[PDB]
Amino acid sequence: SFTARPSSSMADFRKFFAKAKHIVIISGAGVSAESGVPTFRGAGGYWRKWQAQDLATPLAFAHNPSRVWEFYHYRREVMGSKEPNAGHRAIAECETRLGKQGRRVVVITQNIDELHRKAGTKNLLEIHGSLFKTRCTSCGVVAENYKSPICPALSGKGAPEPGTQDASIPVEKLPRCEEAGCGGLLRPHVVWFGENLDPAILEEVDRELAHCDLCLVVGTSSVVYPAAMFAPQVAARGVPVAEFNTETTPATNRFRFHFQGPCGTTLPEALA
Amino acid sequence: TARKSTGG
Ligand SMILES: NC(=O)c1ccc[n+]([C@@H]2O[C@H](COP(=O)([O-])OP(=O)(O)OC[C@H]3O[C@@H](n4cnc5c(N)ncnc54)[C@H](O)[C@@H]3O)[C@@H](O)[C@H]2O)c1
Ligand SMILES: [Zn+2]
């Protein structure tokens, strides 16, 4: 009986929740699945023939920037009509209600979809960037960008079905920098597989993890690093961590609680 | 450990 296996007791989690002064909520793509945004775990991890982790890499962008921009353009256009779900709303409303009591809630998200922002979350660390920002590969400037389509050559492009032909847009016609007449090639302002997360963001993440007294880890596979090690760091300080996922993960047995099921059902219950 | 990767 010694070995702790995670608890499924909602009442015991809610006893910690009632007292918690600083809650960190870490989210991955599962928190947006109920808005109609597929995760990359299964069939939704394919775009044409490629797996998503093979397109979100600086080697794909260096050698076929038109293909990587078609994939991000597809995602931007699909995301424009997507709405926050009950999970994103519970998260946002929890922050607002606890903030009035002087209690802190912060969201550390792997997602680039901005749906936590749309839901009303204020304290948000977007650790992998944003679908709706660009970064210039020449001058480094980061800009918000919601334009549909981002550039004329991408109009009508990005269809996801296997067998769709590549647009093969010449690099000069991909999104270009307009800042002080720079003209450089833009990329998505998204952290890709093989790249370093921003140091300033990581320092803020470390501060929140070190100071929190309760952590939720929601809709993440806990196999994407370094994010996968955030909630185990909190658990190993002896702070309760509650995982909300439709399945178990490689990190589940490190945590105090595991609440199995769709987070749009379990989050409103846990955060009421 | 600042570099993004997949485990397993
Ligand atoms: N919405 C988005 O911005 C979006 C969409 C897909 C992937 N991504 C990102 O790409 C990377 C790879 O994605 P990935 O999906 O392989 O890994 P992930 O870490 O983001 O895993 C998604 C997790 O969600 C769980 N899940 C699915 N439906 C759920 C539901 N309704 N409620 C609770 N949990 C649910 C899955 O079991 C899985 O553990 C991640 O960094 C992820 O954040 C972002
Ligand atoms: Zn520029």
Image: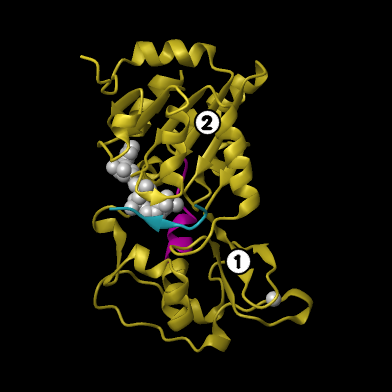
Chain colours: A yellow, B cyan
Q: Nearer the viewer, residue A147 or A30?
A: A30
Picture layout, residue A69 above or below residue A129: below
Q: Which of the chains bears the disc numbered 2?
A: A
The local secondary structure at tag 1 comes to strand
Instruction: Give percent across and percent down for residue A66.
Output: 46, 80
Instruction: Give percent across and percent down for residue A92.
Output: 54, 31
Q: Which residues are magenta?
A: A74-84
Q: Amino acid at mark 1?
A: Thr
Q: Which residue is mark 1?
A: A134
Q: Relative to A190, is A253 on the left or the right? A: left
Assess disc 2: are there few (<14), some (14-19) or many (≥20) residues with their C-alpha within 10 Å of its C-alpha: many
In reply to whether residue A204 is colored magenta, the answer given is: no
- How many numbered callouts? 2
In reply to whether residue A78 is colored magenta, the answer given is: yes
Residue A249 visible: yes
Instruction: Give percent across and percent down for residue A183.
Output: 68, 82
* x 35%, y 26%: residue: A266
Q: Nearer the viewer, residue A247 or A224?
A: A224
Q: Which residue is mark 2?
A: A24
Q: Which mark is residue A91?
A: none
